[PDB]
Image (cartoon, rainbow, N blue to C red):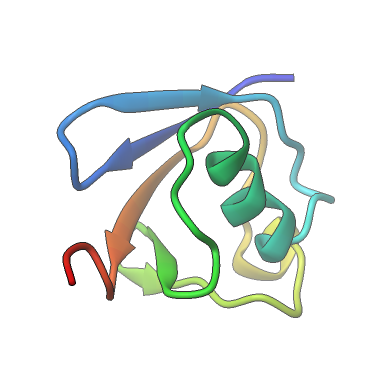
Length: 76
């Protein structure tokens, strides 16, 4: 599998998830190889604020899809 996520860093992560993968997995999938902590990190799909508790399909997200990463807590 293979999808894209544009992070607030300016680089794109290519993560192997599926539309059946839940939002919560995907944020942890980003924390997997990038290290962006899911707790305060949120995904924006084409203007839609993603949230843990539902699948990609709930937001009609598919394979090869491109996500956006916004982090509530970037610096402290």
